[PDB]
Length: 151
Length: 150
Length: 151
Ligand SMILES: [Ca+2]
Ligand SMILES: [Ca+2]
Ligand SMILES: [Ca+2]
Ligand SMILES: [Ca+2]
Ligand SMILES: [Ca+2]
Ligand SMILES: [Ca+2]
Ligand SMILES: [Ca+2]
Ligand SMILES: [Ca+2]
Ligand SMILES: [Ca+2]
Ligand SMILES: [Ca+2]
Image (tube, rainbow over all chains, first blue to last red; front, side):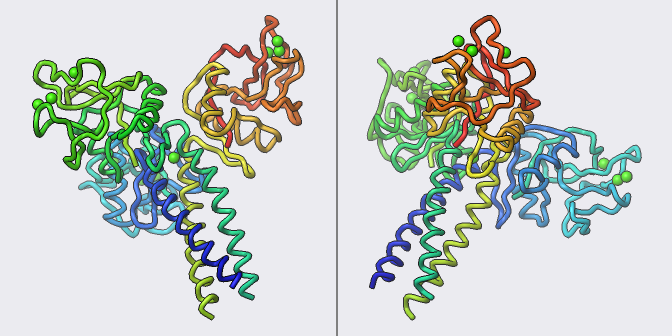
């Protein structure tokens, strides 16, 4: 009966935690986050070159935004629109020109390239940026774009 | 067995309670204010009424709607911190001279500054809260601190 | 049996919460917080004189950054570096010149003074600031420095 009283005690404590946490999830995402599925996009609010942006995300325990579906891309687009700043994606074709991959080396499972892209303009575009219209364009990694990580 | 798993679970819940409590303080610093079961959080920037209202609803909340002196003081704390008057959620856009909450219910509390609301120029249907906590009906097209409540 | 299944169910709920909380904690700390051990450093993003900075932290349920080990100092330095702004620590030698103490009155158990410090320049430097290189310098409390609290 004791273990029973203890189990019922935990049920209440857990119910409380779930309810309190549910509220704080909303508070946290406002105004720089976007939740899509099990993924959370969150912008740092400023721009940085690719390598620096990548470092920020990885050291934070996540990685640069990597939309893998129309839904994720649409969620990421909301942050880009909100900040009115094109953002860097995690993908590059730095290893093999013309072959874009995730930070793990895997090939793209989704893409939303603007017509004609990627075009490796000037023979020097190995990074990818997402516009406010949600379309993608390969861009020089040295350029500064909105830092958006995924967790 | 059960006794062993219940003790493990109890430890898990106690750890979560301590960790969540700490996390709450971190989250609220420096843009949020917890008052009762409500949480006011500022976006840190200004926007006109329509844009600010959309920002809050899209975030799963709504614009700051203080319904008591206690809530008003909490909200005012954020206003003082950012040094910027904020938009409240109430407007008399439907019926002039009658301010209401987004749902449509009449105000259950107000903290108007002397003489307000005065519909200056015949075009003030929105409400702003000053750093002194008092309210003033203001033009909805004006840009004020965005503060939502969750 | 009925209890066993109840414990099994609750534990799944709890471990799911543990996973959700872990994710939201990472999101929360990006880009203005740093966790080290059981301590969490979080910057307000702006500068304030010591007294105002101290009140902001205490009112938030914490206190000004008080690195007590090389590891904590390193974590704090990350925020100072990210914002590129020297930050105030919680320690002062206001009560007894030359003797820096934590808000509790307790003497320092760790220090990372830059060469020549603390020097009490002008005979009025009773506060402590941490540089982007992580080194400390006693600084006049009236100066404005990055506000970083620990929770
Ligand atoms: Ca947060
Ligand atoms: Ca190339
Ligand atoms: Ca290329
Ligand atoms: Ca291109
Ligand atoms: Ca009107
Ligand atoms: Ca009016
Ligand atoms: Ca007025
Ligand atoms: Ca002195
Ligand atoms: Ca001194
Ligand atoms: Ca000095």
